[PDB]
Amino acid sequence: NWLEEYHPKLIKNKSGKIFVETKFSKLIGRPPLLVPGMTPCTVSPDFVAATTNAGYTIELAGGGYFSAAGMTAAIDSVVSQIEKGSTFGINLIYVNPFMLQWGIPLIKELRSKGYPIQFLTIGAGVPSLEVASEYIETLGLKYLGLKPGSIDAISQVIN
Amino acid sequence: EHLEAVVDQDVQRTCILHGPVAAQFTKVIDEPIKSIMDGIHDGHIKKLLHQYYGDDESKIPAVEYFGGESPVDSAVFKATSSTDEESWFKALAGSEINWRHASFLCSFITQDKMFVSNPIRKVFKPSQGMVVEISNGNTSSKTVVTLSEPVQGELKPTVILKLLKENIIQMEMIENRTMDGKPVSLPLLYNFNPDNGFAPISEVMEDRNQRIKEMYWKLWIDEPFN
Image 1 (cartoon, each protein chain N blue to C red):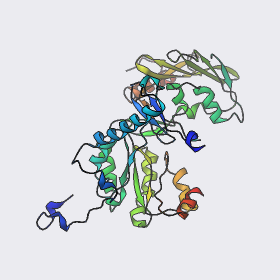
Image 2: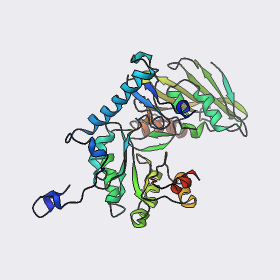
Image 3: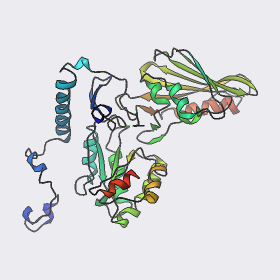
Image 4: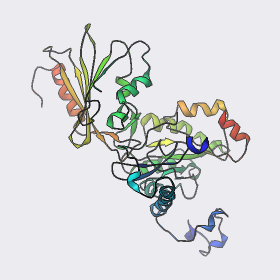
């Protein structure tokens, strides 16, 4: 019964803080809310930082960086702005491989180093099993995100 | 976001995205992100209290640290060839939610804003000959663990997990093949941040290499430490 197996529960923490327990909020010790990757807005590192410092997961706007370093500088900046143990993720694109070939072979390394990144998000597209695979074993990634508006994209993510 | 860089600072020249359905709620200006996210959260909180919890908070459960759960008393355990790993880490994390619940389950520790594999889920990785014991398995403040493994055939304490004041973890990692024969111990300290359920455990990088060096001294040197 979907109304109980997925019942939206509540939680209290030692600090006395309230939390909304779901299958998602419970991987992150953070509410089941976030902000999607938005090129003009989730590209500003200081903003994403001040937000996550409120305790709400965020996607970073990869699309606002035309390189493999500019986004890297934004990373190293938010890092310089967030509190310890904080975290965030990025939003990539699948229709702009050039917007992509930077990150993937860069994401891999930032993780190999162990940056505060913990989730990816492919936007405006969906990959195949073949490609989508490596993202989850090679990347030191907690979880993954997808942006389907189609119906077969959904069958695909289910595959 | 760069009107200054246009012809006459008029925005009607500009391309800006938005949601036609969402504008029905975007009326207040430049309020803090935290303010509005919290408004949302607490609204949900009211809507759930009024229904499922009678609008009395204490009705709520509570937990040491909230998080780390993927969608998918004084005892011992002996690992073996195929001693399953997740079963091992459950047995050793127990059931209660405490520092120990995470130590074996929290996959990542923070090194001053760097997230790296848990060394503990590495070392305690089930194998042959490894036998560990728990004491005070009910109460956490004194819940402690002691792992021993074959040292020259015999078993001897190789690891000691315990809590400290300040909600700290220490692994006293022991090595007994020693110059004087007697063993030596290494204190590896970890801060606990239940307020951060995703990563309440953060290694302390201060004095670290000094401790390691004091170990290696006796491992290598017949002299005092300086």
